[PDB]
Structures are given as structure tokens and as C-alpha cells.
Amino acid sequence: FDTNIVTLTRFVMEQGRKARGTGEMTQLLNSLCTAVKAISTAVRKAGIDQVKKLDVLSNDLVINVLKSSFATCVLVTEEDKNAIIVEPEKRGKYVVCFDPLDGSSNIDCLVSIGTIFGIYRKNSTDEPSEKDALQPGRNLVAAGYALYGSATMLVLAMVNGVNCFMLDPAIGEFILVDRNVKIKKKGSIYSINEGYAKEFDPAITEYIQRKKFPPDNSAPYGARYVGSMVADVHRTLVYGGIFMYPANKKSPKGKLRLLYECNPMAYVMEKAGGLATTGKEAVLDIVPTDIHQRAPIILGSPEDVTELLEIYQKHA
Amino acid sequence: FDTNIVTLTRFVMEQGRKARGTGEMTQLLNSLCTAVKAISTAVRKAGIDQVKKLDVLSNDLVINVLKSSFATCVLVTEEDKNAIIVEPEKRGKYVVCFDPLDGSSNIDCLVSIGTIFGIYRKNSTDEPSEKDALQPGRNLVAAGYALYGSATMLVLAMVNGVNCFMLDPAIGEFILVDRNVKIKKKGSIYSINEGYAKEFDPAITEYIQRKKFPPDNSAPYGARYVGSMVADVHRTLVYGGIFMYPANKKSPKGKLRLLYECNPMAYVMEKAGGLATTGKEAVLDIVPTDIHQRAPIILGSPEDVTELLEIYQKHA
Amino acid sequence: FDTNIVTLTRFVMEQGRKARGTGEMTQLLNSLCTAVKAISTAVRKAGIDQVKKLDVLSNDLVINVLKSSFATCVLVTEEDKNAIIVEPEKRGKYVVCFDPLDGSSNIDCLVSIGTIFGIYRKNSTDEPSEKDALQPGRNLVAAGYALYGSATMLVLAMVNGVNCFMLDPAIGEFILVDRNVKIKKKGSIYSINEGYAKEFDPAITEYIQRKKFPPDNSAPYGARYVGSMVADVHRTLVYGGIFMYPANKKSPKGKLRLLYECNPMAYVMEKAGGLATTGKEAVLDIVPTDIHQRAPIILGSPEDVTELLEIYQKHA
Amino acid sequence: FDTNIVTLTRFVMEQGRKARGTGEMTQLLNSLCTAVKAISTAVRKAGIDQVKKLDVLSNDLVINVLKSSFATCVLVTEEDKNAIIVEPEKRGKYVVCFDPLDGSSNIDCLVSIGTIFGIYRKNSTDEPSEKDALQPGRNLVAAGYALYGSATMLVLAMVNGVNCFMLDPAIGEFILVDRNVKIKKKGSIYSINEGYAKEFDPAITEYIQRKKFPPDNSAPYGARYVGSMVADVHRTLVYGGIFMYPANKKSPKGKLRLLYECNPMAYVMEKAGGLATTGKEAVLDIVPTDIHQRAPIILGSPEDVTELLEIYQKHA
């Protein structure tokens, strides 16, 4: 029976009225929270022609619900090439990008899946809206995600700190669980698909091996790769290590489309002491030549991400 | 798997951005929705020194949660005599009044209980806030309630129409179930505690008896009184009849404190074709001499409420 | 998370072990609780053939759930034409008469509704086993009702006591929350349909006004009528009064069916030390002759029913 | 609301009726599912003695739940010192070895975790009945695990097949969602802790690189390691690969306890037409000598484990 319910939905407000502007941010977030709820459930009854469906049906969901916080100008889905411009009598200051369900049909192993989202603010005036607003990296206002695992944590990283929230299934609300997360600067785990790329790896090959074979008397870093992008970013935020998905030969390297996958993921890391590096540049400071641009990432604890550029540059 | 989730929390927005002002209304409503959720549950696990508690604990709840939509100037609880003035760096345009749990310890018979709420807008300037804003009747902007019965319907009557919403327990959201409710103008049920007041009744005595003994060849009106104010207003909104609680001898007659009980209840009725009459005046058009003023009500279908003033005035 | 989690099952299983029985009671009740649960969810979101459906679905769900426990052999239902005789393969010794959703279409005004059941034992050799196995008067071995109010309460009565379990939705188990439960001598509220029955009430009139404005002098009775058998009876089990539906035209009076509305409820009332008569015959001692026999009922606290009977003596 | 609601129970109850048994299996599994459910809720909101608590609570909850079914007699647990010998009053014929929360404190990174169990039958006369009743190798009558991921999945294996049920939280019942289930010949992902085991991998090395960059020429393997037995094994039951935790120092190698981690899981794998060896001994044929015996395991698709064995031949 527990009186100080600290919901996302008023927490964002407590820093956001201590700043004026327009609500919008919260109306956006809140609406995103309903759809996330919505997905957590149909996935918790997971599987009670056939090809895909769940996910595309939920991209459906994320859209209108995002398009009804009167707070969006334009959306960019993994599922849709082109930005879908939000309507006149529904537009508001903001631009979002989202992979609505990273893992949609790899559920079968009751593995972790997620909704990654990245929010921008349209601002550059009468243009009117159109796809171009999908242009910076290091300027997303608000970014985070939602892992439906044993639970449904929605981690929300903004402007000034990383917060984790938990779905409380008793009352339909995301509740402040940890207030300002910072990353285990080193001491670690490392994660990569060592089948697929082991032969195909480059400078990073010796990287793994001094992370296996200790150039030392150090005990070694443990392997841990779930194969889902959200599950694996989160276990790096929390217990701390280095996650890396390059994918060598064709090189806007891995599946991870920059802009709604590795870019939320980069800012949420960035705000907790996280380096997010292409290996040559910094993932936040890259302008999107095109909105669906696949582009790699190494992220994690700073003294670990940093040992990897010391690999990469005295090398390539 | 069901894509057009029409939640309260954006519905109010769809008429409210089609009007400008400031969000506030929705932030208030939305926050009220969390606390209502919160109560529905602890009541659904009802009863897993001892005197009362549940309710007072929830008045606790309604307050801060109302005091964190930055949208209140002053609150008036059944549970608190005096308006509690909301804080400086938390005040916003609005005044609320609420019986946070009409029926708190009559639960035992798993009967219906509720949260009645009435919202006003402070407007009358630098005064600063203080208890006086609890002054009209027929000017509440927004009013309705929440019955936790077989379900948890939150019926929200505003300015331009009565809406009913249902708690969907799968996703933590109140969903538009009926869009613009209007009252069965007659054809009826009638409800009063015919024990307690039967001897004590006045003009209204013959009223009941021509509602029992048909001054006719009409079949008679059925008895139906649950003894909870919300359960009984709702069954009158829906199947239609007349509810009446006078309580004759001491006459700000019944327990129902005007201002947060019979006044929400009056506007929600009013907006669906509902007469809400003291029996002499009209319950909405009465100014609160004091904020805890008990004061009676007859409400219901118009050709029935109206047959009761035809009782009352060619009589008293 | 307490681990001495006393589910209905463990209650029912301890008791079948004392009695040295075969385990059918336990699986029957277990089956039945699977339906009570899904029906309790059906209703929590109703409003979100087509003239009437939810009753039927409930009745198919309860026959199905009961046939699968091999533990039953005749099933008598509010809905089916005649008895359902269970296939030799899924048989067992019990006989269940049940109403699947009492008050089924009076559920939008959101009041409590429920499922009622009574369980006989088939004692002759073959027949094979048809509806004549519902002759029995008070030879129930178990009876009870499931109440779908703001919590789902299953009050169960058997040879030793009435016990009250509550559905904890955090785990989907009816938990034992209240024990043995006796009703209290006299202490009242009189629950009756005050309209029509007032145009037909004979000895009941005297009783109504003897309890309205008292002759042994002082303090009057309250009235309360929900309009739903399960509801008006359950309130009567917890608070004290008297309940009556004798209503005259429909002259085996009552809508209340003898096998599956009145006898279970009489049983429970009686096991809790409260009585129930016809005003002439005891309800439980009446033999059946029709399985769809309507029978008049009046029940509740002792003193109170005896008062009505003292009056039915020198009267009509 | 479909009424042929096939719960785990009805599955287990049909099967005990074929086998002409006593009904203990059904109540044991029934008890066990009451804990699987509350544990599944414990975890859905963790984050909302004190160094470690949730494991223990789970283990007390599962012993308690198992003792109440009179159906058990020795209980062996990851946590308790020695066997728990059930009081003569609550006894029955089964023997359960179980781990209550595998991966208990690696649950904030929110990954799947679970409860694993194996069920023996006590076949000697008295003793009275102590831990020696856990000699048996593959003499399980039932084994399975409960997986607490984005849905709670209970995979159960017994004499005839592996079957998969899913917890429907709309009713609190494990429902039968998938049947008989065989694993598929070869088809892979190799799941292994690639770090340390790489510094100790003997024949496994050859195998790792024979499956990294292939010699019979073409298409490589993926790696996947969650770091949780239940999780890495369940994924292996649905998709195809190989799983290995042989790890050398800890030389009855394995953290994986023989009675209640490796033998259940071997059983299930084997019943689904996949194998599990030590690389030397079959896991299921190994006799115990300690109830806390650690044993090395490698398991999963046939071809794949046979490949590893072909190599363990001419090797080390």
C-alpha cells in the first residue's frame, strides 16, 4: 500500500518544469511508454501466411501513438526507409527514430528483445518538416530504450543523466529504480560473435586475444554475448565491459543502422561514462549521409573502449 | 495484438490541443489516473490498531500525485477540512475536490467503492491561492469519478460531453469504451434507503408510493439501492432512473458533502441529460458557504427528476 | 512472499485426506477454479449467439472444465435443456448443478456478478447415471459461489464449515483469507426488491414495516438491494441482515431456481449458522421433482428469519 | 476464451490415468507450478539474509510448496546442507532435486533465469528413506525447468516426450503451447564461455576452430553465450546448436551440479533426440556418489555433439 509513486511520467516533468519550454518532451515520452507497455504484454503471451508480423504490427503501434502526443514533426522507423512526416494539425517540435522491436523473431529462445528510440527536436524552421531533420548525431535530446526481459526496464538517458525505470505490472507504470547510472569503468566482460567474425576480424583480433590470453598475470575477461543488441548494451551499462559489433569486410560494417540503433545506444552510454566509437571516429559526431546508414560501434567502459583505439590506431 | 489504443490520456488531448490554453488539464487527469490505478489494485487484494487505514492512506496518495502534475493551486479532500494549498514551485491553474474513496470500509461485501473528483480552475488572480476558490457550483470544468467494481470505469464529464473509460489491466490504461453517454430519460428504477428514511420521508413519500403503487395501469418502478454513492449514480447514468438521497430532519440533509461528492456527480449527470436537484434548488447553482457543506440531491432521468419537483412544490 | 502459501487446493487436499477419499473433490474444485479465474478476467474487461454470448461462453467453459476432471458425471446448467451425462471415459462420482454467470446481463452498471454451484455424490449403482441423481435435498457435499466484484471471492461450504478464499492475481491462486465464518444472530439490513414485491408482499409487508418504523421501541433497519443474488447474499454473509425474494406472480415463486440458485446458497447460509426457508418449508429439505424447479427463498441471520417466520404463522 | 483450456494439470492428469497411477505426479507438479508462478512474479518486479535473499526465499517457497503435497519424501537443494526428509505425515513416493533460481544473482542485467528440477521415485522399502534414494542415474521419471524470461516457459520431460507450456498471466495457468519437440540433427550456434575456457579448452579448441573457420568448405558457426544455464540450454532446445561447460580447474569440472543442473537438462535434451556427455561418460549414466557432485557437461544437437566426440577420441 505504498504512497510516493515516482513515475517516469512526472519525474521527467520535475526536471522539465524546472526549465519551461513546452511539455511536449513528456507528452512524447509518456505516449512512448504506453506502446512499450503494449508490446511487453503481447510479447509476454508470445505466441499464443505466418512470416514475421508481431513486430511490424508494433511499428504500427509506435507510430500513431507517437503521432498522438501532439509533439512530433517526423518519424524514422527501421521498418520505413523514408521518414514519415507527421501531419499539420498534429505536428510538434520533435523528430524521433526507432527500431520498434530489435529481435522480433529470435524470441523463440525467450531471449531479450527491445524498442530502441532516439529523439531529436526539429527546430530548423519553415523547411517545412521533411526527412532532412535526420541530420546530426551528438544532438539528440533524449534517447534510451526498453528491454522486455525477466522484466521491462525502460532506461532513459537525456541531456543530463542516465535513469533506469522498471515496469510495475501491478499499476501500469514505469518506476524510478536507479537514479543516475554510471559505468564500471573497467573490470570486465567483453562481447562479440566470435564465430562469425573471428576469421573476419582486423586490428581487433589481437584485441580479443590479449582480452583472452592475459598479456600477464591478470585473470582473463569473460565471454558473454546474447546476440541481441539491447540485452547486450544493458549488461554492459550495468556490470560493465565492452561490447563491439564491427563486421569487417563491407564496412558501414554491421547491421546496426546508426540512426535509431547505435545512435540512442551511443548517447545513453555517453551520458554514463561511455565511449561509443566506430573505432576510427566517435559515433555521436558523424552526420547521417542517409537515414538508413548502417555503421559500426564499439561501446563500453572507458578504459576498455580506450584500450581498443590504442589497438586500432597503432595498427591501421 | 490491437493497434489503435485510444487512451483517455491522448483523447482529452485531442479536444484540448483543438483549444490551446495549457496542457495542465491533461497532466492533472493523467496523474489522477495513476492514483486511481493504484487504488483499484490495493482494493483488488483487499485485505491481504486496525480501524480504517486503506482510504486515508490513499487520500495520501491522491494528494501528492495531484500535487505533481504541475497543475494544482489548491486541493479540498473529504478527509481534510481546510483546503491544502499546493506549493509555489508546484502550483498551476487548478483547484480540485475529491472524496478519495467513497466506501472505504463497507468493502467487506465486495461492493462497489469509488474516487469522486471535481476540478475547478483558480483564475481569480493574486489572492494568492487560498481556500476561497472553492466557491461556485455550475463552473467545474472537469468532473467525474471511478468505480472499482467487476471492473474500474473512470467516467469523465467535461465541458462538452460524458465519456466512459475502462481500465484495461493488461496495459495500464483507461480506454474509451463509450463515447458520448446520454440518460434513459425515463423508464425506471428508483433508489433510496427505504428503511432509514421511510418514516422520516416528506413530500417525497407520496413520490415513492406512486412509484410503487402505480397511479394506474402502469407496471411499477423497481427498487435497487446498493448503498454506495458511486455504484448507485452509475446504474442511474447507464440503465436510467432516479437516485435520491435527501435525509429529512437535519437539513443540509444527507452525508453527501456537496462540493466533492454531489457536485461532480451533479455535473456528470448534468452533461448527459441529468437533472440534479436539491428538491428546491438546482445543485450546481448554489454557492458553497463553506467547503464541507453537506447538502442533498435528487438526480436522474429528466422526466423522473422533474416528476419529483412537481411533487415537492405543489406540496411544500 | 511468505512461503506457507495455503491455496484452495491445499485446503481441499488436506480435507480429502482426513476423509480418506479418492481425490475427485480436489480435482473438481481445481477444474472449477480454472473457470472461475478466466471468467473473472472475461468480465474485468467486458466493454473492450450475439444477443447473448458471455453467459454461454461461461457455461461452455464450465462444462468443459468440469468434464476434463474425470470426477463428475451429470452436469445441470441454467442454460442447457436437460442434464449433461458425462462420457464413460471422463466420469467420476460427483454431480454438479451450477449457474455460470448470475446476473450476467446486468454487468455494465458494473456491479458484482458470479457463478453458483452445488455438488452431489451419485449413490445408486447404474441407471447408467441420469438426472434422477438430482433428487437429493440437503445432501450436498459442497456448495459455494464465486463473486466477481472488486476482488474475486470464492466462498466454499462443505461438511465442516464455510471458508473464504480470495483470488490473488499476482499468482492466479484463490488463497485462504477467512475461516469457518459464522453469520451473526440478528443484526440488520433487510434486503428485498422494495418496488413490486411491495405491491405483492403478504406477511412480508407486516415484517417490512415492523422493521421500518419499529414497534419494540427504537432504532430502525437499513434497506439494501443490489439486484443480484450472489451480491445480495454475500453482503448478507458478512454483515448480518435478511434477504428475501418471494415475489408471488411466478408462483413457484422465485426466478431462483432450486437446484442451482437457492439450495447452494441455503447450504452456505446454514453452514454458517443462519437459516433459509420458504417461509413454510425449509429450502434444503424440499425434494426436487423438476431439475428446473423454481422455489421461493428467504434467508440470512437466524433471529431475523425467525422473526419473519413468527409472523408467517398468524397470517398468510 | 476458448474453453478447451488444456492446462499443465490436464496434461499431467490425462497421463497419470493412462499409467494407472496414484495422482502424486499431478499434485507434485501442481505444487511446483504454484512456486514457479510466484517466483516468476518475484522476479518481474525485483528492483522495486541481506547479502543474498531472493535465492533463499525461492528455495523456502519451493520446499514448502513441495512438502504440502503429500507426494514427496526427500528434497535435495542447491542451498541446503543435506537432503530434507519429509515428515511421515506429509510423505509420498517421489524424490525431487531442484535448483530454485539458477542464475539468481545475475538478474539486473535482466536476463532469463530459472528453477530446474528432476524427479525420482523411491523404490526400496524403508531406510526409512534417506539421501541414498539419490543414487539413481537416468531413472528420472520427470525433469524440466521453468524459464523466467520475457514469458515464463515450463518445458517438462517425462517418459513419452518433451512438451512446452507457457504461463498465461491472464489466468495464472501454464498452458500447453508446444508438443513433443525434437531438437534438429545438427544446425548451429556453438554456445561456450569463449574467454577462460579458451585458456583451458583441449579437444574443445580444435572443435572451436573447426567450427569457426570451417575445413569442409563453407559457411561458419555463430557464437552465443548468455551466461545462464537455463537460458543457454533453452535456446539450444529451440534453435539447434551445441552447449558446453567443461572448464577444467574446478576439476570435477563444472559448477554444474550433477543431480540438479546437469541430469535434468541431459534428460530433456535426450528426450528431445539430442545427446549429452561428459565427452567421455554419458551424463545420465554416471552414478552419483555425492548429492553435491559437480559434473562436466556438453549437450545439444546430435551431429554437433558427435562431432565433438569424434574429436575427443584422437586427442585428450
Image (spheres, coloured by chain):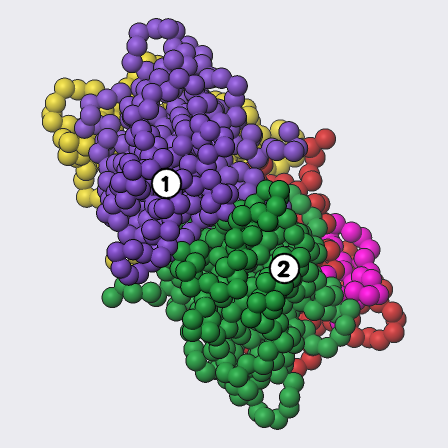
Chain colours: A red, B green, C purple, D yellow
Judged from this view, the residue extending furthest toward the bottom is B126
In the picture shown, does residue D295 fall above or below D180?
Answer: below
Q: Which residue is mark 1?
A: C203
Residue B30 position by quadrant:
bottom right
Q: Left or right: B195 with respect to A201?
A: left
**Residues in magenta?**
A68-93
Image disc number at residue B307:
2
Which quarter of the rendered picture does the C terminus of chain D lie within?
top left
Kindly tell me whether residue C108 is visible in this rendering: no
**Which mark lies nearer to you, 1 or 2?**
1
Judged from this view, the residue extending furthest toward the left is D127
Q: Nearer the viewer, residue C148 or D12?
A: C148
In the picture shown, does residue A62 fall above or below C202?
Answer: below
In the picture shown, does residue A23 fall above or below D91?
Answer: below
Give the residue at x 56% y 52%. Answer: B210
What amino acid does circle 2 point to?
Glu
Give the residue at x 56% y 64%. Answer: B298
Q: Secondary structure at mark 1?
A: helix
In the picture shown, does residue D210 fall above or below B294?
Answer: above
Check disc 1: other Cα within 10 Å, few if <14, some if 14-19, many if 20+.
some
Q: Residue A109, position in %: x, y? A: 53, 39
